[PDB]
Amino acid sequence: KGHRRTYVGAMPGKIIQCLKKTKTENPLILIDEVDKIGRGYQGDPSSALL
Amino acid sequence: KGHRRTYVGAMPGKIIQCLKKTKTENPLILIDEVDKIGRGYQGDPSSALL
């Protein structure tokens, strides 16, 4: 999701980097090794990824 | 049910995330697979669900 820009060192969430790097709006973004997400600091990140 | 919010990562139990999502106050919550609620851990979440 990126940080608010209020926190020290805040940077845009991971997707924005690729949206810059590919210089396009239709990358073939690829999730990798999905079997083992869960049990995050907020329960799980995965919900927002849904 | 969530946590006390004096903890670092506290988030409300799943229902309130739903209510934040579903704009209506009376949506069609759909829990599924009550049959295999995890209950080996000391303290049974079933009680909370009751």
Image: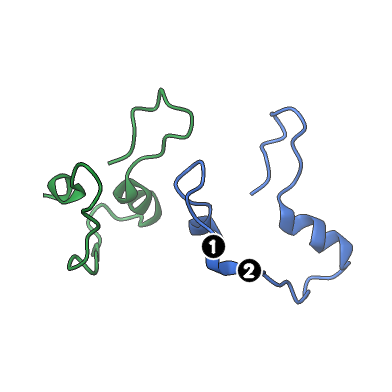
Chain colours: A blue, B green
Chain hosting mark 1: A
Measured from the top left, where is residue B8 in percent x and y? 48, 28
Q: Is residue B10 above or below residue B17?
A: above
- The amino acid on which the numbered mark 2 sits, given as a three-letter code, is Glu
Q: Is residue B12 above or below residue A1?
A: above
Q: Which disc number belongs to residue A36?
A: 1
- The local secondary structure at tag 1 comes to helix
- Left or right placement of residue B36 versus residue B19 in this view: left
Chain hosting mark 2: A
Q: Which disc number belongs to residue A33?
A: 2
- The local secondary structure at tag 2 comes to loop
Residue at screen point 18% across, 47% down: B44
- Left or right placement of residue A44 versus residue B39 in this view: right
User: Residue A18, located in which quarter of the rendered image?
Assistant: bottom right
Q: Is residue B38 above or below residue B45?
A: below
User: Residue B21, located in which quarter of the rendered image?
Assistant: bottom left
Asked if labels 2 and 1 share a chain, the reply is yes
Measured from the top left, where is residue A31 in percent x and y? 66, 69
User: Residue A10, located in which quarter of the rendered image?
Assistant: top right
Residue at screen point 47% across, 50% down: A39
Q: CA distance from mark 2 to mark 1?
A: 7 Å
Residue that lies at the very extreme toward the top in this rendered image: B6
